[PDB]
Figure 1 (tube, rainbow, N blue to C red):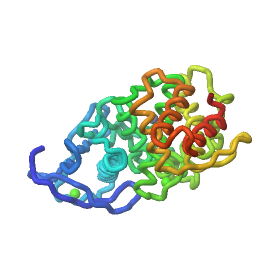
Figure 2 (cartoon, rainbow, N blue to C red):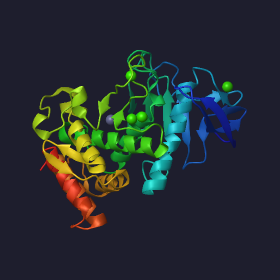
Figure 3 (cartoon, rainbow, N blue to C red):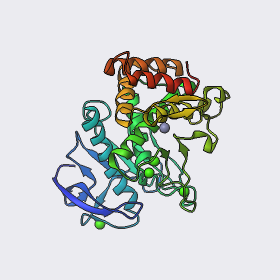
Figure 4 (tube, rainbow, N blue to C red):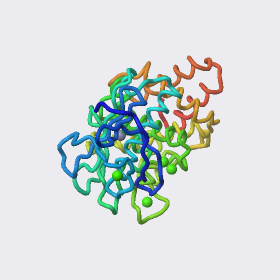
Amino acid sequence: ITGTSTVGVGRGVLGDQKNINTTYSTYYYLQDNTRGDGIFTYDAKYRTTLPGSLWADADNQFFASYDAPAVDAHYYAGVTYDYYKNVHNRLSYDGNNAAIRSSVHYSQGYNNAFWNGSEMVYGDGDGQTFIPLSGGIDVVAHELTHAVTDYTAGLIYQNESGAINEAISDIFGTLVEFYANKNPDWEIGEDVYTPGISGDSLRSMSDPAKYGDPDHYSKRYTGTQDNGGVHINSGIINKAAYLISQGGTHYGVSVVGIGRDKLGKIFYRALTQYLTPTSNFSQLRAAAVQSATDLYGSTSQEVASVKQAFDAVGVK
Ligand SMILES: [Ca+2]
Ligand SMILES: [Ca+2]
Ligand SMILES: [Ca+2]
Ligand SMILES: [Ca+2]
Ligand SMILES: [Zn+2]
């Protein structure tokens, strides 16, 4: 829409108050003209037709319970855009400031959220397994990172390349959660998963086996479910990334941590310069080693830690 840029206020899924960028033109719309070609949030009104209607509001105050998922989709897309711009110098997901569009209230009782190739889509959850999925900043950033991967490495969504694709989304989702300093951790989806149980999450990067995902290449899933295990075998790479950052000893192999910032620079470089659509785990190891070599030198501690981490999860 064409109108005047302004700032409104509302409450997210978790009850927290936040300011959001809006546009005025008769109604106030969830349209943020301050970032790239804009961030636009739509109401799918419990249907599956997309994108739905651009979110319009009469007084620029978004404190209704139907408003919550839209406030957080809109706000967390802006935080993810800022992370990629300020930390990695990347303008939006295509690198040229493409508009980011999200629809909320998709379908009824839908326990998922996803990047469909053109925009973000968020279910409200059934209220037991999940509450509206845009209340999780790591979920939002995980899904928007699929758009980055689509425009760069183009990892296909199956077998080892799909598991790399998911892991990359969990890694950067976690780094955005630390960047926003929103009670950060190495777990995925803990703010929106099972409102009645405390302490759990969908996946864990620091200990993937806590939920039964593999934490070593010898335990990888080899069947056909989940497109060949893209959500299951991502635990092997998530554990490697957690060790590079934080360090630790895993299956007897010791890794000195180099921290989150360097983790993010090595993986962003590997993703945007060396991975291809059919890269497998072994090629991800080579790409991460070459990236760390590019950035810090072949005899750095950073290269050594990347190697130990992949050796700790059995990826040669
Ligand atoms: Ca209102
Ligand atoms: Ca957290
Ligand atoms: Ca998290
Ligand atoms: Ca829970
Ligand atoms: Zn994903």
